[PDB]
Amino acid sequence: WTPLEPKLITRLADTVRTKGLRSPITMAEVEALMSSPLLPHDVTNLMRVILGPAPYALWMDAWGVQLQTVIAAATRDPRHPANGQGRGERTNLNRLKGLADGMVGNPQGQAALLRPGELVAITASALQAFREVARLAEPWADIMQGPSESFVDFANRLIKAVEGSDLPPSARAPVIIDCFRQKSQPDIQQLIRTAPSTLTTPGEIIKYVLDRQKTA
Amino acid sequence: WTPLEPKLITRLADTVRTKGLRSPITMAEVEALMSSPLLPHDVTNLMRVILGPAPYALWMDAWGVQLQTVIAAATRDPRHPANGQGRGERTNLNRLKGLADGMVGNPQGQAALLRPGELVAITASALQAFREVARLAEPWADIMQGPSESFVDFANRLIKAVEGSDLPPSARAPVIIDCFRQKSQPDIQQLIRTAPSTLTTPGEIIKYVLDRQKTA
Amino acid sequence: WTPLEPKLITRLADTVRTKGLRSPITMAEVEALMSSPLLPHDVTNLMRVILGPAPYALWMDAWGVQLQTVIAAATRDPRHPANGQGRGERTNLNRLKGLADGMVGNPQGQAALLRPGELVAITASALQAFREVARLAEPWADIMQGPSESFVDFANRLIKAVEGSDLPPSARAPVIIDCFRQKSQPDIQQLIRTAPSTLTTPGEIIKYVLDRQKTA
Amino acid sequence: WTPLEPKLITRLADTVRTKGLRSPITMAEVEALMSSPLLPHDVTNLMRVILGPAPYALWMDAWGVQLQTVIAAATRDPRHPANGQGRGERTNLNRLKGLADGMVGNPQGQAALLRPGELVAITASALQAFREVARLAEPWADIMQGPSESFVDFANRLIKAVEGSDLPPSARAPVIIDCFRQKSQPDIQQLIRTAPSTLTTPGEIIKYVLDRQKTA
Amino acid sequence: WTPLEPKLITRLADTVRTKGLRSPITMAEVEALMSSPLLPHDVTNLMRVILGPAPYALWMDAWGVQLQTVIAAATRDPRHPANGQGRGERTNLNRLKGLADGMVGNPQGQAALLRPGELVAITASALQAFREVARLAEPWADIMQGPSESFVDFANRLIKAVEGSDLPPSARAPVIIDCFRQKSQPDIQQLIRTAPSTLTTPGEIIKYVLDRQKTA
Amino acid sequence: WTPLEPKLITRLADTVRTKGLRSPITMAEVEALMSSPLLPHDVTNLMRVILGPAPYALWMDAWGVQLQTVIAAATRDPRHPANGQGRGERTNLNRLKGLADGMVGNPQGQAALLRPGELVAITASALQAFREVARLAEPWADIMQGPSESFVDFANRLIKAVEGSDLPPSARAPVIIDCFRQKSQPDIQQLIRTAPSTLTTPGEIIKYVLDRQKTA
């Protein structure tokens, strides 16, 4: 086990302190420090340092809930990269939260007994929990493209607000498309309307609009 | 033996000077500089440099107590990674504190005679002693939510004061909940009281209150 | 599998944030972080972090198209470094995009089953897709030297717009020369026209004009 | 072949951006990054990144001219550290500019076939070309000492304009002296005129004037 | 001979400038730069750079005195690691201070003729002289706890003044305890007096007082 | 040959720009970057970068004069560490200033042919020339110890002004002593007057005064 640099952690903590929890730069920095699969000890101490007390409580709750969903999916499929083939490799929440035997407080033993699939599942769970808490602490149908705003900024803002919302995963693309069509002030509205081809994906709409946009 | 960089030690000392002993960034930095197993000379000089005189005295006391607990566990189990199989490898406190023969003041001889299990035990003992002294050096039942204070600030302050107190670990969540219910001025009190669902976690209470709070 | 440093990724993300997608320094930095053959997981997370949402959608599209061209060339030649000799080693797009069995979400298994030729093909495809999206996200024949603008600023702007355009590499110097001659308001036009020597390079024209320019 | 750090290149590019091309700190930094013998690929990409488009064109021109002078000296002496003893080792400009066979676009093959004498000659040529372009990209006989200006500022400005001009090196000191005597408003003119000793160096004149100047 | 880095020397000089001569961090840094056996030239230039003029004079005096004590011990024992077996290897102070023939001003010749025992003796002498001058340049029995001062500040000040004084190392703890008992205004005096347990360490006294102190 | 870091040179240039040429911190920094023996190329470029045009002219003059004094001492003693035993190793000023054959503009050849004694003599000459120019560009008998000034600051200022003046080297110590006795306001005057021992050195006077000074 190798610990994360306290210099990077201090810089990330100050980033969270000045920019907040929800800024795209903060989420990018968290994704950066969430690159290598971390042990429960690492993520727990990281969130202890960068988050205040109340956001840390919220994050512990959300992390537990997401890990429980993961364990339900794991008991629903014996081919989980955290599981094994026999029943003796089934992964309990004590092993995920670092509470199992030989792991409590010891990061070396933790790194010894944990699986790489376990590590990546814990890491993805912690990232999703961070996203939930950030969305909770401090509206996609109210987003309009400003008269002076460019289209890539509007698309970034809209996709951010739609993906970081309460919609099901299978309802984000149609909503993003229909919001591109009805928002995005009438010049781009007519540009999308008069599309000789049928655009059936937000990426394709973005590419088309970026090609044929009125340079100004 | 290779000494730690005085640049890292100076940066850590300034971190302790500005952030304090108990900040999570400071504990992360200490864990960072506590990564490789250190010899008693290294940890002793490190604490001499980063800590003031009175915290250094407290830390010497706490380190001695923790090492004594370790030696009691060692005489309670002949399979300690610091011990050996025969009685001639039993580890005395003079060998742990660096006071044994051939070690006093000489880090090279120290590194020669010491075991890796000895080093990791000394290191873990020093880390626990640092935690104790940090918790000791610098009231939750007196915390009220001010008339103008927001709820996340009140929750942060309350969770901080409850977790940094003398309560057992298994009594913090019920106390935090019952303090959310009885403190947190009567508007939020009635908001929590009339909860159609049963809230059984501080994170869930915080989420509910943040959702249904009176925007003002 | 070893992950890329989040410090390098954070520095690259800030580079993309300040300099943009198309600057030569940004492309050099991407080439730097594109040195070792990356697994689909690595490149996917890298583009997720450094690119915004809409450029990331565009990049996913372009990467898919380039990988499809690669797979067409692969079915057009059984000697692809990603292919094998028999038909059982033919590489499907599920194996290139990391969607095949034993690879979805698991970078360790990914690194296990993938070929080095597969890795380098994926990497080159991702680099070409990044170039396409950068050229798409953000006109030389409309550039005139303003009445008050100096000549070095005009030359900088013109060379920038000509080299960052859709012209072939072998057509940039003649175009830059003929734009120096026809733009660059009639004082400098006559200064270049009455050149006793024949100027056959943009650098030589710039040097001549800087020597004989009307100091004002 | 090992590439130069993009961090050093970014720092050097920002140095060139803020200080300019001609500052002594910039030339020192270039000499620093010009320490190990670089391959044509390295120097070419370095100048592509640190220099703008028009200075890069000028630098390509100057580098070609200096390399041609080097090749003329090489055909004038068969004992060039780039040449060999037989005629089969004669070095063509395609091999110096990296255009020869097995080198175009490939830095590894470049490093394979190139000689150390070739590398140092290319490097010195590139440094001289950079100096020429820096002197070219950015009048002594019009410099007067202002009524309110101090003498050290006037001397600095005059020596700067005289040394950064088209005079031969052996004509700068007499010109600086005779400009000290005829410029430098009549109080200092009479102070230099009535010098009991003969001052035959700009430094001696500066020292004398600083000693006997009218404190005001 | 290899010189010490001017970067390390500049950092050490600024450390001495901000922290002073007597801080434990400064002595640690000096011990760091005093790791390899230095030639008289190195130590002399080092003290010339890091110390001011008057401390440098004091240090020259103290270094001479300590070297004279070393030479007296050397003439009192022919088995000095600087001496040899015959009388022709006896080490004169001109050879220690670098004043002997073939050494004055030349570090290369110095490194040639000097012995490793000579180097380590010179180095230890210089370190002891630095300690003396630091103790000399910039009262524990006069320290009282002010009426408004907290107890941790008083303990810090007292431990600082007692450890940075002329007492033997084995007499600091009893003095600190007996000064806690007789200073530290009568409320804390009575608090320590009525201790049901016997406190036999400054850290234990500090912990007890911090526990049972009158919150105000 | 290894060049000096442009980062250190930039920091030193900014130090000279803000603090000036004569500040003790600037002279300490110059001594730091003057630690290893530099080649004429290094010192020449260093002074070109850190000094303005007029101070650079003055410094070239002073460096030439000091090197000429060195060469006179060298022809006055055939045992110069730059000289050799035979007449064929006599060192000409073209070899010291880097103007000799095989050295003009080439630092590698310079480092090849130069002697270490040559390097240290050039370095000491350049340092003395820098001191002269710094004293010249922007009075010891006017120095008084202020009513509130400490004694070590007064001693530093006085020794600085006396050693950086036009006095012979054999007249500095008596002047420093007699200035300690007559300046240094009457409390310290009487403290030095009533010295039971005879103080015959500035260091001894400083030590005595620091011992018996009135703590306040």
Image: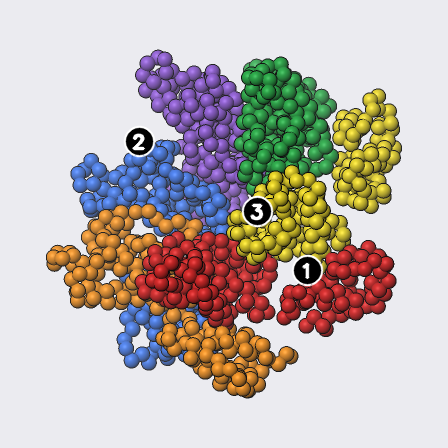
Chain colours: A blue, B purple, C orange, D red, E green, F yellow
Question: Which residue is tagged 3?
Answer: F114
Apparent side of residue D103 relative to residue C194 in the rendered image (left or right): left
On what subunit does the disc labeled 1 rest?
A: F
**CA–CA distance in space, label 3 to label 1:** 28 Å
Circle 2 residues within 10 Å: few <14, some 14–19, many ≥20: few
Observer-side mark, 3 or 2, equals 3
**Which of F186 and F159 lies nearest the eye of the viewer?**
F159
**CA–CA distance in space, label 3 to label 2:** 69 Å
Which residue is painted at 51% across and 36% down in the image? B5
**Against C104, is F83 above or below?**
above
Q: Is residue E26 visible?
A: no
Apparent side of residue D20 relative to residue A33 in the rendered image (left or right): right
Question: Which residue is tagged 1?
Answer: F53
Tag 3: residue type? Answer: Leu
Apparent side of residue E161 relative to residue C79 in the rendered image (left or right): right
Apparent side of residue C86 relative to residue B35 in the rendered image (left or right): left
Tags 3 and 2 on a common chain: no
Which residue is painted at 68% across and 48% down in the image? F67
Q: Quadrant of residue C45?
A: bottom left
Q: Quadrant of residue F29?
A: top right
Element type where label 1 sits in the image: helix
Decide which of tag 3 and tag 1 comes sooner along the chain. Answer: 1
**Against F186, is A73 above or below?**
below
Q: Is residue A37 visible?
A: yes
**Which of C124 and F45 lies nearest the eye of the viewer?**
F45
**Against D22, is C142 above or below?**
below
**Against D69, is B53 above or below?**
above
On what subunit does the disc labeled 3 rest?
A: F
Observer-side mark, 1 or 2, equals 1
Q: Residues at badges 1 and 2 in contact (C-beta under 8 Å)?
A: no
**CA–CA distance in space, label 1 to label 2:** 73 Å
